[PDB]
Image (cartoon, rainbow over all chains, first blue to last red; front, top):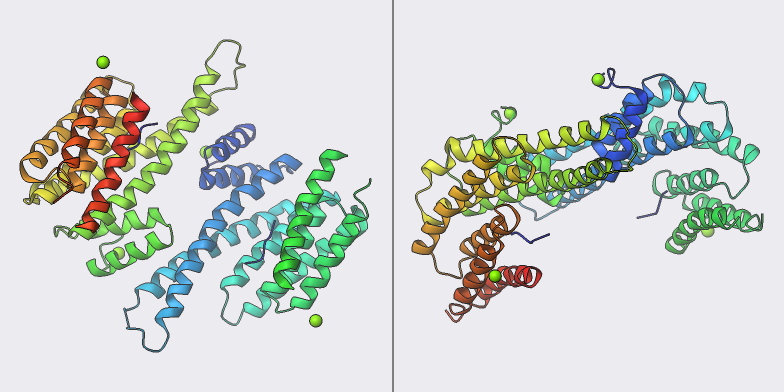
Length: 5
Length: 5
Length: 235
Length: 235
Ligand SMILES: [Mg+2]
Ligand SMILES: [Mg+2]
Ligand SMILES: [Mg+2]
Ligand SMILES: [Mg+2]
């Protein structure tokens, strides 16, 4: 659920 | 651009 | 082929998982394996077959349109020449799309259509045949484009005759068939007046039949709104 | 392989078309062919490589999660047994995902990383190495899960050391690397406090450097907002 880039 | 189904 | 070793019920179960996972290539291969088991399909299995290939070919058609547009801009005055790469890649996607259409038409011809005796199965498969010849017609340019259009028209017309005799005007398969045949007239056969007449007539006749369940009411009116949407676009 | 006969510039041009067409499988194969030409990649070509495989593996990870969830529900008390089909199909997607990760790691090892001398290229590829070991770690369960996690951690740590020495705190590659290493700590290494400390420190140090163009300001603050978003999620 964490955002990566 | 016409809709089909 | 590769699905020959898997049970029919397992191919169906995995097709439903693939849909949940939005893995439509898997789904179509599973459903192609289930068809090649040789047994007729239930109504639910026909819908899974339809959903899988519609999504596969729908992505290919979207990509083809992006590439065909780039290609056409590349062929205008003042545009710098960029080599054969755009035409090559457009041709690559186009060939893949045609291969999926041929796969579907091949399943319908061997042997889904000839074993379909009920109206609901027979109209469903003939509509599919018309749809996938129509997808071929979208990208056809050579000496077969006329014959592809006529194969689409013939399959749609046969499905229409059966559906008017055998189904009520509100039946979702009958409605969806008339919608797509009207899209064929407008977008493929250069017959926008025939498209509009078909859409208006189909809508009015369904409207007069709605009074005959709330669940079926919702199913029919959903498709009638697509007819309405197109009429608003076309007029 | 299959791209051996095509010019490097043509593979790059077709990779850009495939992106426009949202054909990310094509894009990755084109970019894999361009890498295998043996020349180092420009900054723009590195970004195309990254976009292509991120989208390929991103779809596979999304499907794996849908299937793993169905599988876990299938293994609870009171759930009816449905046969091996869910585990089989989850394993099928999982193996495909691992194959893409191995393909990427293979490109990095042969020979992108050993030829990257500049900070921007070397940190970019080491971050990629960490990301794709992290995607392997998401689905690892056996006796190699510890070693996969440590390969991810090692690549991220090497990239961090270089980026702190060689880049300003606002550099997008440095920011994106720190974001993903913080996601590694939180989601993979069970170190949520290390994740939060890394995210807060990375954000504050970029904030103090923003005063040094409006275009680069927009690039950095975009990634800082992702750090902010995660901090809000995590605390
Ligand atoms: Mg088999
Ligand atoms: Mg008129
Ligand atoms: Mg080749
Ligand atoms: Mg604490």
